[PDB]
Image 1: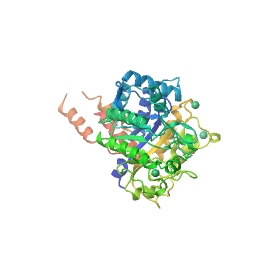
Image 2 (image 1 turned 45 degrees about the vertical axis):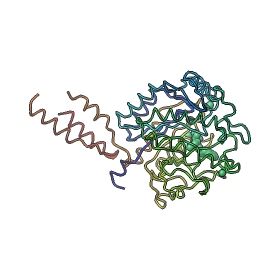
Image 3 (image 1 turned 60 degrees about the vertical axis):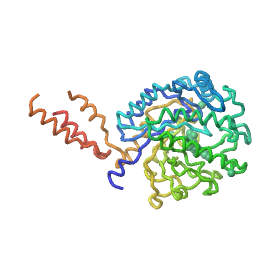
Image 4 (image 1 turned 120 degrees about the vertical axis):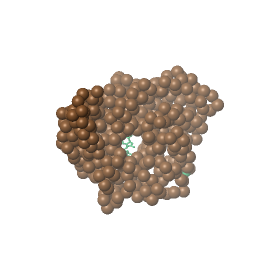
Length: 410
Ligand SMILES: CC(=O)N[C@H]1/C(=N/OC(=O)Nc2ccccc2)O[C@H](CO)[C@@H](O)[C@@H]1O
Ligand SMILES: [Br-]
Ligand SMILES: [Br-]
Ligand SMILES: [Br-]
């Protein structure tokens, strides 16, 4: 599309701060790097196996009773340490996420939070047991460590209330809320979660829960987002899903993980955030470890087109996306986070797609903040400010720099 259409697309960096602790300063630096490279958003997983975000008030009402704030905080901390007791820290505070959002906003960077369920919720499962909610776990080939039992009302009522509170905090602070839903019970079904749901006639109950979280998002003025996995599994539609969800599409799946195609979901009216698995990097991952190692991720930022949805060949298949997301995962969270690796990956994606990414506007904001005299000198500042172009992409840094230089002189 046009110059305007390209720059209006979302350019997103995702950070798995669910499995692994990131300090507020580490995340601010990511925001900084995103702002310079011309991204529009930071996607931040806060619940993803671990749950590394606590609000000031964590009081929950569900199941006819209340769970007091201190007990919820204690339970969640215990759940999170039980998944991984990160030496670097456990959870971000309300004050810290509030500051990250404000800080990002000052650099025209949005934040997109993710709180995962009913899969990738190890911490919430143990937390619920510490609060007296027995057997919240899905149980298939074994008792799952990651996933909630969809028939357990007590657990479901609790989790929904908890996600409601988080959504309450983000309401009016962010546009988007990602409720996840990927890889249901992968640990207990050898990554055949959806097949197991259908087998047990529980997929309809998955949709009921997915639709609930979508509705919850919308009634709090948040645009819902979820991963594509659970939606219209195997291109079948006898179970219906909320059409308003923004789909974070990462893959059509693997042998016998028979996900809906992007073609099929588009046909149902869905819009996509292009979250191609091609751009995945797992901290510390090398060729010998499996998929999603650094060298290949870096290669793919050039090799896979910006608009190419996974399992499709662009432009032969050309489906509406709202933008694209590159993803940093923490599967082994004891692995050392090396900022420079993430920065190289981010830079490569921006460099290969200069039409989509903004120019770096940081020097401009620094020169503007220096403003507080004759009519001649004030006239000089008048025109130099008028000459500023806020619409420049990454191809036009030199051009922006000249405009800033002229402002400095004035
Ligand atoms: C939505 C998503 O990307 N989920 C997981 C994810 N899924 O990627 C897969 O390839 N998952 C998968 C593998 C085999 C069978 C089914 C799904 O990738 C990341 C890096 O490994 C994990 O951190 C994520 O939790
Ligand atoms: Br079913
Ligand atoms: Br590598
Ligand atoms: Br680990």
